[PDB]
Structure formats: structure tokens, C-alpha cells
Image (cartoon, rainbow over all chains, first blue to last red; front, side, top):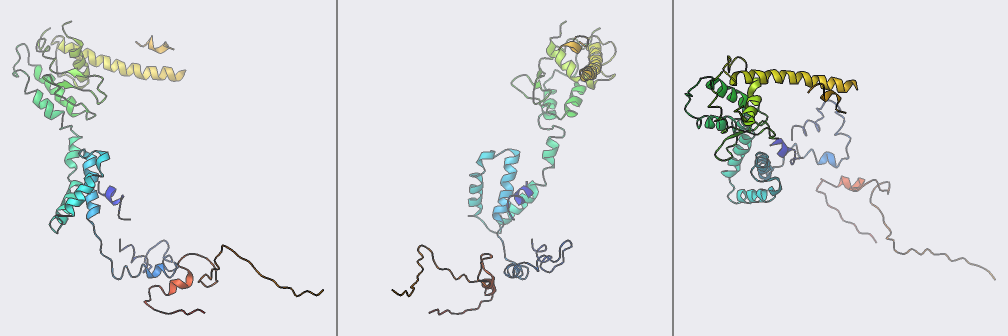
Length: 267
Length: 49
């Protein structure tokens, strides 16, 4: 967000007194040959460099930052830029003209948090979930305490699938997405229909089934035993996921050999 | 009866140039010679007739 300001403005002096002096490597005999007008319009630069006025540049180094995180929309950085320039062209001083400098050489460096924001989704995945888990009932359900293993598999899923896995709080009911596409929106305040079977050995509306199928991959010997339903189903969903991988590769193979066809004797 | 040829040379809409370079030619702008009296804050004074 700065070199995009460098690569939007500011067309050096070492590179100029490295060429006039003929200290380059590839073609030293470069500056000598130019017309004796250029060679007298580049020698009086690396002999008495001309000052500059950097405000615009680093101000453009701030706009290109805002509009890349999300404030000032892409189409408004022609009013924001003028407004910022005129503000910093009023109150300017070594005061502000520096306070910028720090802002521009910190905003491009203090981007690690932003990177973190999208590397553990600690923006709407764990802060939301670790909020929703605090809206759950007490952590002592009656039947079993396979509860905690499931509720931890949920956190692991949300933390190890950065894709989007956003956890909205679309009003009273917090709902889990499986991707920004969102074609597996399962309601996470509607598994207070699993605070039923948390411990037993057709009452699951697929919404609950959707959550089970969504996390299952991330369950191993955790939700465990023959803890009824919740146990097996998870195991059966994992088995079905493996079989689905098998059938996926099989169908690609059988359609690369060559119409419903494979879809029948696969499904 | 006898002839004493006269002879002219109309030219209209054209401004005689005298371009100022060496090979009185045109190899650019900031033309050769000009380029010399560039930097040198030198000063001169024509006087054509």
C-alpha cells in the first residue's frame, strides 16, 4: 500500500551519479553518448540535488491504504484525497508533515494484525463462537459430557478452515457458514436440539444433521463410544465422507475414460 | 521579333524558413547548435539586414 503509492507516483540520486559518473555495469558508455544538452541537464542534478515536496506522495500512501481495508470506497478516493491534502496543506508543519510519515510507515507495517485477522479468522469466527459458546446452556448437560468434545471440535473447525467460516449473529440465533458462498448455512442456535441426545444409545432435523456432516471430518475418537446416535452418526458421516471421496475420484476416472451413467452405479 | 527572357517565382502561403542548425537541416527540436548556448549563461545579439 506504499509501493503502490511509489508505483503511482515519483517516476533517485545514487542511480543518477552512478550513471553520469559511468559506474554502472551493463552499459557504462550510456550517459556519455547522449546529446550535450541532456549531459548538462543531468550533471547539475548530482552536483546540487533539487529539493522535493513529498506530502502528496505519502498522502497518496494513506488513501491507498484506507481504500484497501475498506473505509473510503474505491470511487471516493478523489474527494478523500483532496480533503486530506487540503487539511494537511493547512495545518501543515514539521508537526503534521511528520505525523504523516509515521502513519504511512506504520500502516504498511502494522498490517500483521490484519493478516492475523484472516489467518485465524479471529474477527468473526472465534470471537463470535467464543461468544456463542458463552450463550450456550451451562457446560453441564444432564445426559453426557461428550458435549465438550463436540463443542471443541466446533472451535477447531472454525479455527482450521479460514476460508470464510463466518459466524454471524443474524439476530437471536448465531448461524455457522461453511463458506462465503454460504450454501451450507446451518443454524447454531438450533442445535439446542442436540441438548437432547447428548447422551443416549429421527428427532434430528437435518439442520442438526447439517452441523454433524459439517464437523464430522474433524472428529476422530472424540465424540465417542456408542454414545448413541451422536456417536455413531458422527462415525457414519465420516465413513460417508470417505466413501464420497472414493466415489468422487471414481466418477472423475469413469468420465475421463469416456449421460447419467456413472451417477447411477455410484449413488 | 527578339526575346529577353524575364523569369519569376511566385510562392504563396509558405514562410521561407532558415532553420538554425548546422547541416541547415532538421534532426530535432533543441537543434544542434542551439543546444550549445544552453547552460552557458551567455548572451549575444543578431542584426540581420
